[PDB]
Image (cartoon, helix red, strand yellow):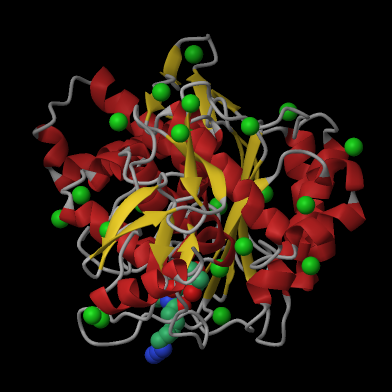
Length: 454
Ligand SMILES: *C(=O)[C@@H](NC(=O)[C@H](Cc1ccccc1)NC(=O)CCCCCN=[N+]=[N-])[C@@H](C)O
Ligand SMILES: [Cl-]
Ligand SMILES: [Cl-]
Ligand SMILES: [Cl-]
Ligand SMILES: [Cl-]
Ligand SMILES: [Cl-]
Ligand SMILES: [Cl-]
Ligand SMILES: [Cl-]
Ligand SMILES: [Cl-]
Ligand SMILES: [Cl-]
Ligand SMILES: [Cl-]
Ligand SMILES: [Cl-]
Ligand SMILES: [Cl-]
Ligand SMILES: [Cl-]
Ligand SMILES: [Cl-]
Ligand SMILES: [Cl-]
Ligand SMILES: [Cl-]
Ligand SMILES: [Cl-]
Ligand SMILES: [Cl-]
Ligand SMILES: [Cl-]
Ligand SMILES: [Cl-]
Ligand SMILES: [Cl-]
Ligand SMILES: [Cl-]
Ligand SMILES: [Cl-]
């Protein structure tokens, strides 16, 4: 089954490193293709013949419950576009340990491992990690910052689209995330590029490989393809108050006589500040509660109302032609990554991610809890003490004060709201260009509307 071959493949790679070091093979010698083939074959025979003890992070009751869940409820994914394939990884947020996974609908019918082997764009689940999370971390935005969703074009003249919408106007970060509007994510990433932020530094600390960081649609998942296991590791980082632990299934390999061939070594990395991570947790809580892009909270409330009252956060994604849907879920204890799609990349139904994957993942979450009642935990995500709280205008996401609007000094007042920041000073005073992004026309239409209201 999936677990046997995933474990065997990883143990063979660790045995390869061990044997080459044992036999004092130089890194140069190791570049020789014939030497490499010999050491791969030797590693395979050592595992096959050698009576090694492989210790995995797999919780057998949970992993077994996940296999029964996809066997019993995988048909809930079938949406009239043929048999829908699936990958899920359940990860301990404090360690990066993989407790269980779903490799696909049925190993016996299709052996492709959709948790560890298959790479697809994570689509709009990129946004919290690569755009908004980094912007907050760099003190370029807070929880109630305003972004432009006004119509705008990619460099090649194509409109930035969201379903059939060419865009609306100004909106909060919260609305931008709840809906997964695309234009606000585009502007956030353009701001990071313009400011020369080392985005690669963040993404590589979490083990992502992105070839071209200049892609305009990077936050929407253009120019990124990931395994479910890797992408689960990204969300583990946000859930774990910004501290990455490298994903692993193997914790140790020992010879029969107890000599250590390999032992996983924890190497925690603070990728985002605690302020940034805990702010993003609060935003991703509302993504699920708002139910705009996923029915997950409705599905889970019906299956298991007590589990639905755990502190769920997450994010959805849909690739361009609905070929791939994602739902990433966390409680403080665990992250569960979910992909669905077709092996031949053809389109899913329009609602496959919104409804079908949401219902299936509610069933998977329920099966995990029934197998291991305390595993999700009852702990809440909470704002770090280092978070800065700023009273800002609802209309500008910045502090009340004076702005020049067409000659005339204007006193900007009105509804205020607490905005969470991950810098020292918090939110700035309202300036004319108060939003992330927008044209001089957009600002003319945003200020008309705000001036109208004073
Ligand atoms: C996040 O899930 C958003 N998805 C997108 O914006 C995707 C990004 C993407 C595109 C291709 C591969 C991988 C990722 N793009 C679109 O949805 C664009 C829609 C098509 C409009 C242009 N029509 N044409 N031709 C989600 C919230 O939209
Ligand atoms: Cl398996
Ligand atoms: Cl496998
Ligand atoms: Cl176990
Ligand atoms: Cl893809
Ligand atoms: Cl434009
Ligand atoms: Cl909203
Ligand atoms: Cl970069
Ligand atoms: Cl990657
Ligand atoms: Cl670059
Ligand atoms: Cl591993
Ligand atoms: Cl031995
Ligand atoms: Cl910190
Ligand atoms: Cl809710
Ligand atoms: Cl709903
Ligand atoms: Cl309860
Ligand atoms: Cl989405
Ligand atoms: Cl297919
Ligand atoms: Cl809180
Ligand atoms: Cl404060
Ligand atoms: Cl303040
Ligand atoms: Cl500051
Ligand atoms: Cl900007
Ligand atoms: Cl303009």
